[PDB]
Image (cartoon, grey):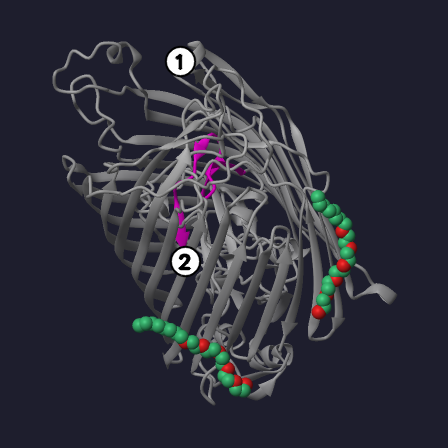
């Protein structure tokens, strides 16, 4: 719809980049196609489709309208065969925006290598949850999004922390707009489990080994969250929701030009949610604020400054699971799903804030440079109190553990990179080269020396959280940890033939951790990157890649000799086929993959039975492990108003014992989410549904009172969602979401410190949304 334009005659490359910007659209073009060409002048209010063909007059170009993207091509009379994965330069470094795309499949993405590529062009497993998918299913936070993410399993540590698995491993890599955070442990990492989606366009999950842009990190995957950006037209909405257990949510989002020419633009979002829960005496208020301004210093240099803020403020938090598995005599405890072991005053409050600045420049080359500066804060205030241990006792009394943790981590990041195309042997290729630095500082106080507290409660069966609050006494411990990460990286994408694209790159990493532990250091560590994509027809490509990652170990992971273990490392080997239909409106993929891990920390049973180094007292042992499995997915348009996202993933991970490991992550899982937009008389109704299933999962847990190990199983189960929206008015809609329709009762945690957690019972959410 009608946009204000001002793009004078210049190199067609520049014009296309200016167009993408002014029109809030991604423009993809082939560098050698536009190189000796110039745009014709556009001036005024114009519909973006009229506008582009007017800009291209005289250039010989054609336009492929593809939602939030256009692609430009210059056809010849000649044409000996098509080059589907030809090197394309792009106007948006983050990819295609998903907001207003109406689709559950992404456009282009840069999660893999920093190069802006389509899913078919990326030689790794890339899954995305689109803006519209979030809107349709009411996914309001990162936990809601992970639960809906093909290939991910969400399980619970406690009421205010979940765990995300992929391919056998806990995910501990998070990016924001491609900027990696420090996530060594829960210190640096408060609130990462809890981010509200109000401020984000989409969440993009790269699965396998993602050392190339993450730097030091975990195996499994990275989760990349892309922030909402300002726009050239005014727009906003307000949203109100009410759900089971007095779950109330409001949200405001406003975006647009802040000056008459449109050279400064901003976006603001505020969101607030206050809920109780099916769990007794648990509640959580969350607040989120977001502000971003874009200044055009000149038509090819842009400055962006931005801040965000999220406070997560619960009451009735637990430390570990919702209730203890065994009672005092070893019998399994049986409790309502409402049971909550946390005390009334117990709280794991968690907060995050960022300030950030970027500068982006277009070099008359077609080359583009970017500088990203981040100040990030991850704090926590955690006076925790829960029933814990083998309780009840026969008289129905039980005992509380109570500990208080406060702290804050401050991080500063600088990321600079350069990207562009280059000719080599008569063909067009592209390259990213970049360097990064992060310094991040964790400071904290801990309190376990309670003064004159009576930690017993007379009544377990009717436990309510109504116990007293202890004198925390003085701090037990001060934390001072500093982690410093330096990286340098480069990837090149060679268009070797009309059908074959070769990916060569890597990262060199420097990682120092400093503080009250003995210093931990890796210098000059190389993380390789190799992949290829081979086109088979207009529809299908096969691909293969070899990718790597490492993480220096926590300092308590020492060995026999008191030496810190070598870093936890791994390689992902992947081969697959990806399909593309309806001009990128539908994507399919099928992959086989193996993760080889090395230096996985392992207890060291034989030493640990009788320490013999006066030196250490609980040494570990560095072992190998392997993930084997395969994965199928589909996302996009099945028929004109019919959108899906679905996946199947199978895995088994074994360690150097032979024995299966990560046995809480099911060996088999499936998601299908879908919605349909009617036409004719009912074109204002959208209907929708979804199902997630997982096979058997289990844990070995030790029953102290009976002195024996036990298997705990969660049999396979299904979960079903349903959804409907009516657009009653141009400006007003109403939705209902129903979750776990069949009220399946099941576990999200069995075995975390000998405790258990239930998943959510049937719950509804009702919302209205107002678009100005
Ligand atoms: C150093 C700290 C960095 C903080 C940056 C904070 C940014 C906050 O800016 C918010 C700007 O949002 C603009 C919201 O968009 C509304 C524009 O509409 C203009 C009024 O409409 C007139 C008629 O259309
Ligand atoms: C254990 C409890 C589970 C209960 C199961 C309930 C499932 C049945 O739900 C049926 C939903 O129909 C209710 C219709 O309400 C319409 C919602 O309209 C939204 C209001 O719009 C406001 C406009 O400003």
Q: Nearer the viewer, mark 1 or mark 2?
A: 2
Identify the residue under disc 2.
Answer: 311
Measured as percent of width and height from the top left, residue 304 is found at 37, 72
> Is 55 positioned to the left or the right of 657 in the image?
right
> Is 724 positioned to the left or the right of 213 in the image?
right
Front-lying residue, 731 or 302: 731
Q: Residue at x 47, y 57 (%)?
A: 286
Assess whether mark 2 and mark 1 are in contact (beta carbons under 8 angstroms).
no
**Residue 472's quadrant in the figure?**
top left
- Residue projecting furthest to the left: 614
Between the C-alphas of marks 1 and 2, the distance is: 43 Å
Label 2 sits on a secondary structure element that is strand
Q: Which residues are magenta?
A: 152-176
Q: Is mark 1 within 8 Å of ligand 2?
A: no
| Magenta region includes residue 171 | yes
Instruction: Classify mark 1: residues with Cα within 10 Å, few (<14), some (14-19) or many (20+).
Output: few
Measured as percent of width and height from the top left, residue 206 is found at 47, 44
Q: Is residue 16 above or below residue 548?
A: below
Label 1 sits on a secondary structure element that is loop
Query: Quadrant for ligand 1?
Result: bottom left
Q: Main secondary structure of the magenta part?
A: strand
Q: Is residue 767 above or below residue 261?
A: above
Identify the residue under disc 1.
Answer: 657
Measured as percent of width and height from the top left, residue 342 is found at 44, 39
Q: Residue at x 26, y 33 (%)?
A: 554
- Going from the N terminus, do you reach mark 1 or mark 2 first? 2
Q: Is residue 731 above or below residue 673?
A: below
| Magenta region includes residue 663 | no
Measured as percent of width and height from the top left, residue 560 is found at 19, 17
């Amino acid at each position: 719809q009608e946009v204000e334009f001002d793009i004078p005659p210049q190199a067609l490359g520049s014009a296309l980049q200016e167009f993408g910007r002014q029109a809030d659209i991604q423009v993809l073009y082939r560098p050698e196609e536009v190189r000796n060409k110039r745009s014709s002048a556009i001036k005024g209010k114009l519909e973006p489709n009229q506008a582009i063909t007017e800009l291209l007059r005289g250039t010989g170009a054609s336009v492929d309208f593809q939602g939030n993207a256009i692609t430009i091509s210059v056809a010849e009379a000649a044409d000996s065969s098509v080059d589907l994965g030809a090197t394309m330069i792009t106007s948006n470094q983050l990819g295609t925006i998903t907001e207003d795309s109406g689709s559950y499949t992404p456009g282009t993405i840069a999660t893999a290598t920093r190069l802006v590529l389509t899913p078919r062009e990326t030689p790794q497993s890339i899954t995305v949850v689109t803006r519209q998918n979030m809107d349709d299913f009411g996914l309001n936070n990162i936990d809601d999004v992970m639960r809906h993410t093909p290939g991910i399993t969400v399980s619970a540590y406690d009421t205010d922390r979940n765990n995300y698995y992929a391919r056998g491993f806990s995910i501990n890599n998070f990016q924001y707009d491609g900027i990696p955070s420090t996530a060594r442990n829960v210190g640096y990492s408060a609130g990462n489990t809890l981010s509200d989606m109000a401020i984000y366009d989409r969440v993009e999950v790269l699965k396998g080994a993602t050392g190339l842009l993450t730097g030091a990190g975990s195996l499994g995957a990275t989760i990349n969250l892309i922030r909402k950006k300002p726009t050239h037209e005014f727009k906003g909405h307000v949203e109100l929701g009410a759900g089971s257990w007095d779950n109330y949510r409001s949200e405001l989002d406003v975006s647009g030009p802040l000056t008459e020419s449109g050279n400064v633009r901003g976006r603001a979002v505020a969101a607030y949610q206050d809920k109780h829960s099916f769990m007794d005496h648990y509640e959580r208020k969350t607040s989120v604020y977001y502000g971003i301004l874009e200044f055009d210093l000149n038509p090819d240099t842009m400055l962006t400054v931005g801040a965000d803020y999220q406070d997560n403020d619960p009451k009735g938090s637990g430390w570990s699971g919702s209730f203890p598995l065994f009672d005092s005599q070893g019998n399994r405890n049986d409790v309502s799903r409402s049971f909550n072991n946390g005390a009334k005053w117990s709280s794991w409050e968690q907060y995050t804030r960022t300030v950030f600045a970027n500068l982006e420049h277009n070099f008359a080359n077609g080359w583009v440079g970017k500088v990203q500066l981040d100040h990030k804060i991850n704090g926590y205030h955690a006076p925790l109190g829960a029933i814990m241990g083998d309780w009840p006792a026969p008289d129905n009394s039980a005992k509380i553990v109570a500990q208080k943790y406060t702290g804050e981590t401050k991080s500063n990041s600088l990321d600079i990179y350069l990207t562009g195309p280059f000719q080599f042997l008569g063909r067009e290729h592209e390259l990213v080269v970049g360097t990064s630095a992060s310094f991040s500082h964790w400071e904290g106080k801990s309190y376990w020396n309670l003064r004159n507290y009576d930690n017993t409660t007379d009544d377990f069966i009717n436990w309510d959280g109504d116990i007293g609050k202890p004198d925390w006494g003085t701090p037990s411990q001060y934390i001072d940890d500093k982690t410093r990460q330096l990286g340098s990286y480069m990837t090149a994408r060679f268009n070797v033939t009309d059908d074959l694209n070769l990916f060569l790159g890597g990262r060199v990493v420097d990682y120092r951790v400093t503080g009250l532990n003995p210093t931990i250091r890796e210098s000059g560590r190389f993380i390789p990157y190799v992949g290829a994509v081979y086109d088979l027809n207009d529809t299908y490509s096969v691909y293969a890649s070899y990718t790597d990652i490492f993480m220096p170990q926590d300092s308590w992971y020492r060995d026999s000799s008191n030496k810190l273990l070598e870093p936890d490392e791994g390689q992902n080997y992947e081969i697959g086929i990806k399909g593309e239909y309806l001009d990128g409106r539908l994507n399919t993929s099928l992959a086989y993959f193996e993760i080889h891990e090395e230096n996985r920390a392992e207890e060291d049973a034989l030493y640990n039975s009788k320490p013999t180094n006066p030196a250490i007292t609980y040494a570990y042992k560095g072992i190998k492990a392997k993930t084997k499995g395969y994965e199928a997915e589909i996302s996009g348009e099945l028929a004109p108003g019919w959108q899906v996202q679905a996946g199947y993933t199978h895995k088994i991970i074994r360690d150097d014992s032979g024995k299966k490991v990560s046995t809480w992550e099911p060996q088999d899982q499936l998601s299908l989410y879908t919605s349909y937009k009617f036409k004719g008389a009912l074109d204002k109704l959208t209907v929708g549904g979804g199902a997630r299933w997982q096979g058997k999962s289990w844990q070995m847990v030790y029953n102290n009172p009976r002195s024996r190990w036990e298997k705990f199983s969660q049999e396979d189960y299904w979960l079903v969602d349903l959804m409907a929206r009516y657009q009653i008015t141009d400006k007003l809609s109403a939705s209902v979401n129903v979750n776990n329709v069949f009220d399946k009762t099941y576990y999200t945690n069995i075995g975390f410190y000998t405790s258990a957690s239930y998943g959510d019972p049937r719950n509804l959410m009702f919302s209205t949304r107002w678009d100005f």
